[PDB]
RNA sequence: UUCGAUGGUAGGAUAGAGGCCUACCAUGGUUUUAACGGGUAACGGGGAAUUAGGGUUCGAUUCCGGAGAGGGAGCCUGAG
RNA sequence: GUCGCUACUACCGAUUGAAUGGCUUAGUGAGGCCUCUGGAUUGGCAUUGCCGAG
RNA sequence: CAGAUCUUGGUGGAAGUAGCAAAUAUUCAAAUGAGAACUUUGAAGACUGAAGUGGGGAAAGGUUCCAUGUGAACAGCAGUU
RNA sequence: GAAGUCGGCAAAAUGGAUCCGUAACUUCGGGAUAAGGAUUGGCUCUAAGGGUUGGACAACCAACUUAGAACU
RNA sequence: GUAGCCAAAUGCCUCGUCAUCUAACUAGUGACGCGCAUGAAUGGAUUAACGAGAUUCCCACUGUCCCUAUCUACUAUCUAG
RNA sequence: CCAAGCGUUCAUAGCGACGUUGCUUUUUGAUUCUUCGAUGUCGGCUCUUCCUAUCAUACCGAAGCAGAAUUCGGUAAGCGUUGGAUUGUUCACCCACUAAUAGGGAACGUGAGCUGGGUUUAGACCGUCGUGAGACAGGUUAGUUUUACCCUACUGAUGAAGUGUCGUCGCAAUGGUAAUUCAACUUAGUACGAGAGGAACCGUUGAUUCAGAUCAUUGGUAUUUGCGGCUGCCUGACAAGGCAAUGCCGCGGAGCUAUCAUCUGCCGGAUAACGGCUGAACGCCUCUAAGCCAGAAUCCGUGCCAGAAAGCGACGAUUUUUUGG
RNA sequence: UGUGGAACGGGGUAUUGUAAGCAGUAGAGUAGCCUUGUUGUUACGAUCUGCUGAGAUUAAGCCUUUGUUCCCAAGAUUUGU
């Protein structure tokens, strides 16, 4: 007796390590042939977290027309490079890839993806493909026409520009992004003109848009049932430990059931968090990335001393509200929402009033080096 | 329940068996929290209250007439810090409450010490007898 | 968007920084961090602690 | 009798004497002739009532003295 | 005298008894006074810092 | 003889598994040696802290005492000790 | 702040010394360190409490305590 | 069954009746006694002090708990034997 | 099931005797078929799953102005069913909250999971009985809770290739799945209603429980032995250090972590009860016989988690003038 | 052998709280020495003040670096339609 809800959710099983790291899109948004051709996904890198202050526009709320403080996550999103197109035909056994067409020239970043030791390799990855592309230019057109004639789903191959990111990893992340819009012919044509071309973050997503964040969570290693499933700690008198489940099963069935909490892996799992609102899409070529209409100080989106364990964000970035799966510097997937949003919270425009740029390496109290200079005056090493 | 509308979530700091001070001139010196109104069902979880809650309490030290009986009370101060919606963490120097009726009208007439803003908005009768707010 | 001043160290307090303590004598104190709050609870004197702006103002540090 | 209760020395403060206060030195001072404590439904006296004498009761109240301006505490002006 | 029966008084009285006023216990402590600083301004010195009131 | 929780002897799976975690703590260089984490020397860092991990005895043991050599068995790792 | 648990199990809290103060009950011996309070460092001083010894005294040598004060 | 004593470590009925504490106790204590089946050196009653005896309550205090979290050393792990 | 009846008045609104037909039994009892070369034995804690004989939540029907309240009534077990004083207890009774504090099974679920409060017969006291040793439709006190390193199950972690090799990007058969409830306000003083009174669809703002993440802020943690402070001893003194099994104290970045902090948590089809349409049978009527809609928190899907290690697809390069191909 | 890596150094960001040394009579005061001072020298003295927002640490899971010095142009195994 004394009923209580079960510990944990059976939908997130098995609690094993994810087989991937990038984070894949399990379902792209439903295609519409009326809206123009556009992308449905993007890749970025989690630079860190900060907090903002903004006026809450929500009639009927207690804090209506009053400032609120909210935590946000910054994801660096430099433009991605489209290097290929993949067509999928709708078979009675699912979606099947028919053929893949690549660009004539591929960068070193994307070419590193096909190798474990690129430096020791002979750098022969698309040499014959480029030769076929330059020989007479009929096979590429034939394959593109095949994708146009057949196939119902078109996905472009795009890779991140990790070179202009402070990450030590030189290998770029490659991903298939489904192309939604009118007609397969326009999708293939759009891919063809975008070969060896960069797609920016603001062309894919816009301000106040609700998106989904897909990524692998922070690794936690092995963990007991107390922290893996949130079970009750056993009394202090418990012999042979107290951080376990007292009863893991009953007689008949003479087996341990799959619904009983057990110790094991507790982290590094694939997740997709829904309904993340875009608070700001900032560019990498302006000095007012973190400046608002109520704070005219020319400052960029970077804490004092740089982002902790990440560096300096000099590219385009997003300011999704709340938290996102995965640790800092992990690659995250941004996907268009599969649902329709009509609530006040979803449709409320966001106008930031202040963005914190103080150091996250401690109890920072200065937003900018100029503010630190004015407050502290002259120091011993400062004057001499 | 049904004080002036809705109150934002606040950090609970006054569970059952907590003895807080009495911040009115009803004649009671402390309030011993017996139960908290609005508490749901959860195994082993002790009901707890924040500022502006509508706990039931008994008088442990005070007038014998006020002792040995249950009475509604509203929590006005708590030691545990809670976060406002504007990202401000605040707390008081003591845990204090005031004896009220089920409708929320204070049995006393004057409130000594500051009163939390959330309690003031929720219960207008408390705000009238209160002095400074926050 | 206002910026407060710490009641102990005198440092500028941006929103979402430190804590707020309201005393029984209806006085409001804003502490920039736990160090300032702990020293206040320990009854340390800001005019005595060398790193506080009140000490610097009293002693005319920096001219 | 500590954080001054008894006396001595010195000093400070007071308009002035003074354990009024301060530092030191001795343990002293009152008391069954009632010290100390408690109640007073106690401001005190000239005086009033009863009237053999002796006594008993009262005095908030036209005069004298004391304290007070809800309760203590502190101070300026001013000879006060 | 006993029990039976009625109104009333006082004591003890568990309830670790409560509450009004005084005597203390430890901390905190407004305000005036004295005292150390303190220096908006004035103040004899185009001229300068010195007595300073403050 | 197939049994008797049979007798004696030998040998298995468990298995290169449980385990070899009380008593704070070792490090550098040199010598010997085929071989050095355990031998010796020097240096450094520590502990027992006089009711001691010090110096002696009673009972008990019986050569374990000393010198010179050995490293087959033991010193649950090693060994030049 | 015991709401845990059969049960304050375990842990925490108290703790030395000096100065105040200490109830019911009692076999008058105790209870009692009842309970309940305050102080404690460093430095510089002050006062008092004892030994032999050169012509009312006396320059040493050889000594440890107690109490108090200022400053920090 | 006298003096005493009691739902007592002794009462089945029983969670006896009344009072007290708690917001609430079948607990505890204080009273009552047709006491199944208390009782006077098979000792009755009371008793200061004492008790690593048993029971109830209060203050201080605290991860016992709300509700768990963090840190250190030795294991568990891997390796050589 | 039958209906004598009660139900100002109507046999079944609803109760409903006497009988009768059944289901269950966690009440002990009955027998002795298994176990005495050995199945650890109550309660409590923890944890998972299953049933409906449904307490609440969802949608319906029955009467009466409405609004409450009743049949919980018809489907429905998807999702919840609490905190305390007491009982060792099962049960049961009180204090409150809550939408509700519903009932059971799983060797009367769960001791190589815990505890040992019950039993716990060794020590000891009492009551009754016995001459006695000793006995109990009894009370009380103190009394060792062993072992997994084996197989399987479960939780996590590697892993060979004949079907070319090594990589990149993928599909998804299958298995699992998740959200839940409440308050206030606008509807609205509106429908209704002689009167007082008084809803509902929807929408908005919040909140409870649960689930998955994260560390911007706040709190906690200290071997950052990072900085500073303190005691005893030691290095002749200062300085700088060491020991005191982490010497102690204050702060303390980074990390971890908190329903002590923050973020997020959909809609499509098919239905159950039930309500209708065209419509016969049974020349009419009637949801049903054929057929068509509507319709529950129901079922299955979208989405979410894993990815068959013997399911599959597309793409890339193929031991270099030595050798292999 | 490359927008290569490493070890240091610098800068930034953070933690603590003002380093050692010198000087000052600031210092509660205490003893000697002198022409005898409204700054008398000298000796001891918890502490205080100024150089000093100083000093120390700062990746070990912080950021940055056109600074300095080195290093890598190797070895072994497997794999064929």
Image: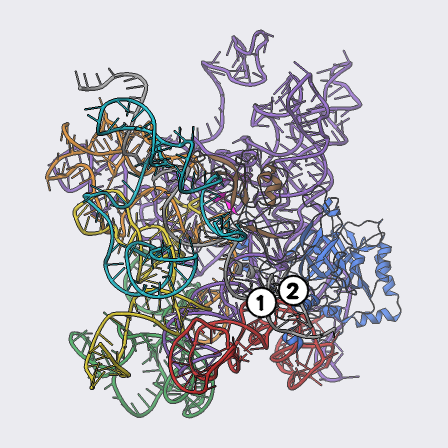
Chain colours: A blue, B brown, D cyan, F green, G yellow, H orange, I purple, J red
Classify mark 1: helix, strand or loop.
loop
* Image x and y of residue H50, in percent: 23, 51
Q: Between residue F31 and residue A58, name the one nearer to us.
A: A58
Please name which of the two marks, 1 or 2, marks the residue nearer to the observer.
1
Q: Which label sits on residue A108?
A: none
- Mark 1 nearby-residue class (10 Å; few <14, some 14–19, many ≥20): few
In 3D space, how far apart are the residues under numbered discs 1 and 2 (Cα atoms)?
20 Å
Question: Could you tell me which residue is drawn at 71 percent across and 57 percent down?
Answer: A354
Q: On the image, numbered disc 2 is attached to which residue?
A: A359
- Mark 2 nearby-residue class (10 Å; few <14, some 14–19, many ≥20): many
Q: On the image, numbered disc 1 is attached to which residue?
A: C51
**Image check: D74 left or right of A366?**
left
Classify mark 2: helix, strand or loop.
loop
Q: Between residue H51 and residue D67, name the one nearer to us.
A: D67
**Image check: I76 left or right of G22?**
right
Q: Is residue H39 above or below residue A105?
A: above
Q: Is residue I312 above or below residue F10?
A: above
| Magenta segment | B13-42
Could you confirm whether marks 1 and 2 are on the same chain? Answer: no
* Image x and y of residue A253, in percent: 49, 46
Question: Could you tell me which residue is drawn at 84 percent across and 49 percent down?
Answer: A33
Q: Can residue C42 be seen from the camera position used here?
A: no
| Residue J32 location, quadrant | bottom left
> Subunit of mark 2?
A
């Amino acid at each position: 007796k004394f009923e209580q809800p079960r510990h944990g959710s059976l939908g997130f099983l098995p609690r094993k390590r994810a087989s991937r790291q990038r984070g894949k899109v399990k379902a792209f948004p439903k295609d519409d042939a009326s809206k123009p051709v556009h992308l449905t996904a993007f890749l970025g890198y989690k630079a860190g977290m900060t907090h903002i202050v903004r006026d809450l526009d929500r009639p009927g709320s207690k804090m209506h027309k009053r400032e609120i403080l909210e935590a946000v996550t910054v994801i660096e999103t430099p433009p991605m490079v489209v290097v290929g197109v993949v067509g999928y035909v709708e078979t009675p056994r699912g979606l099947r890839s028919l053929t893949t067409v690549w660009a004539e020239h591929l960068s070193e970043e994307v070419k590193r993806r096909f190798y474990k030791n690129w430096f020791k390799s002979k750098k022969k990855a698309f040499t014959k493909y480029a030769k076929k592309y330059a020989e007479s230019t009929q096979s590429i057109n034939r394959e593109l026409e095949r994708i146009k004639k057949y196939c119902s789903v078109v996905r472009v191959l795009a890779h991140t520009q990790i070179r202009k990111t402070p990450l030590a990893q030189k290998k770029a992340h490659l991903m298939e992004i489904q192309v939604n819009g009118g007609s397969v012919a326009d999708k293939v044509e759009w891919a063809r003109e975008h070969f060896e071309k960069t797609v920016d973050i603001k062309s894919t997503f816009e301000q106040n848009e609700m998106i989904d964040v897909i990524g692998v969570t922070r690794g936690k290693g092995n963990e007991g049932t107390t922290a893996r499933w949130g079970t009750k700690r056993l009394p202090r008198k418990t012999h042979r430990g107290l951080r376990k489940v007292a009863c893991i099963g009953a007689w008949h069935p003479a087996n341990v059931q799959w619904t009983v909490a057990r110790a094991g892996n507790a982290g590094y799992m694939h997740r997709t968090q829904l309904n993340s609102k875009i608070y700001r899409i900032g560019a990498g070529d302006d000095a007012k990335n973190a400046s608002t209409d109520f704070d005219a100080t020319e400052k960029r989106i970077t804490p004092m001393g740089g982002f902790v364990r990440y560096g300096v964000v000099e590219n385009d970035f997003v300011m999704l509200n709340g938290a996102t799966p995965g640790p800092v510097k992990r690659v995250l997937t941004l996907r268009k929402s599969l649902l329709t949003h009509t609530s006040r919270k979803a449709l409320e425009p966001v106008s930031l009033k202040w963005i914190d740029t103080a150091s996250k390496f401690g109890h920072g109290r200065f937003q900018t080096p100029a503010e630190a200079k004015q407050f502290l005056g002259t120091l011993k090493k400062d004057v001499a | 329940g049904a004080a002036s509308g809705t109150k934002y979530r606040m950090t609970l700091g006054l569970p059952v068996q907590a003895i807080m001070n009495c911040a009115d001139n009803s004649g009671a010196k402390n309030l011993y929290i017996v139960s908290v109104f609005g508490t749901g069902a959860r195994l082993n979880r002790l009901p707890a209250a924040s500022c502006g809650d509508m706990v039931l309490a008994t008088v442990k030290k005070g007038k014998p007439d006020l002792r040995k009986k249950i009475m509604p009370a509203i929590v006005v101060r708590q030691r545990k810090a809670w976060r406002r919606k504007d990202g401000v963490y605040l707390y008081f120097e003591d845990n204090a409450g005031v004896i009220v009726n089920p409708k929320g009208e204070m049995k006393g007439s004057a409130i000594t010490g500051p009163v939390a803003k959330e309690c003031a908005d929720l219960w207008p009768r408390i705000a009238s007898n209160a002095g400074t707010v926050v | 968007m206002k910026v407060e001043v710490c009641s102990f160290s005198g440092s500028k307090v941006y929103p979402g920084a430190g804590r707020l303590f309201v005393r029984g004598d209806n006085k409001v104190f804003r502490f920039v961090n736990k160090k300032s709050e702990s020293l206040f609870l320990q009854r340390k004197n800001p005019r005595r602690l060398s790193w506080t702006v009140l000490y610097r103002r009293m002693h005319k540090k920096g001219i």
